[PDB]
Length: 73
Length: 52
Figure: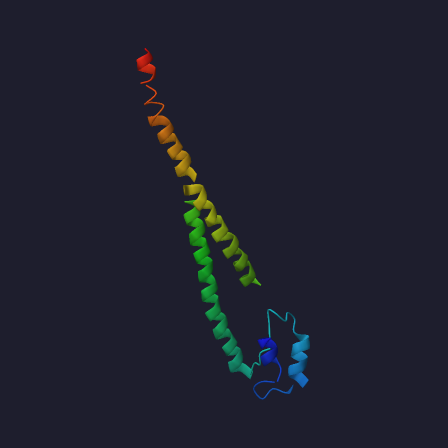
């Protein structure tokens, strides 16, 4: 429910009709909710997260890789 | 899109390790059947040099 909890009632100062439409427009609602993004530094933002994200992906992939090596060895 | 694969990677990886473990301890034990079934083919070397 909690999704339902935050996604409605609107965010940061984002207009309510647009915020709506991102909800309908949303390609992939469980995996995803609409999150307000704010001009360039925000994209900067996103990227910082992406990188943050990138490193952890890489690593976990390494963990699977190590376990597989152990099994094969 | 990649993260998901990562998931069924984790999956199926620790069920591979459930695998091997198992097959691992299996090999001990098939192995132990081989130390017992051996001591005692003889001590079946009594029972047969007695008959002799």
